[PDB]
Length: 21
Length: 21
Length: 27
Length: 28
Ligand SMILES: Cc1cccc(O)c1
Ligand SMILES: Cc1cccc(O)c1
Ligand SMILES: [Zn+2]
Ligand SMILES: [Zn+2]
Image (cartoon, rainbow over all chains, first blue to last red; front, side, top):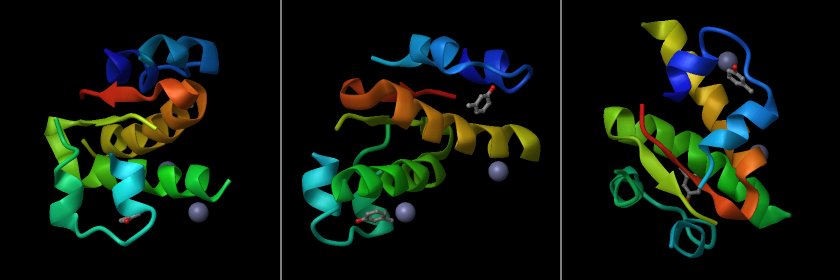
């Protein structure tokens, strides 16, 4: 999930948008 | 919802927990 | 933009209050 | 541990900004 993906390496705003509704 | 309820008047910790999963 | 700014603080508070439960934030 | 907790705080602020009127769920 989001923590595994984006607290291990930087996520861009495009990558984070994948976790929106 | 939360904005109507807690940005017009201060919400307690107890009131905010209403919005937890 | 005050409602936007208020929502920013709301989300940080829900993060802290909800803990492992997590939360939902719908504008 | 602590760094994950702190990371999560930044994550939620970013989701708030990017998700806009859609909003989001934060499920750790
Ligand atoms: C914007 C942001 C916050 C937290 C971690 C990330 O990878 C990215
Ligand atoms: C703690 C908190 C933040 C923002 C609005 C509120 O009513 C309460
Ligand atoms: Zn502020
Ligand atoms: Zn920080």
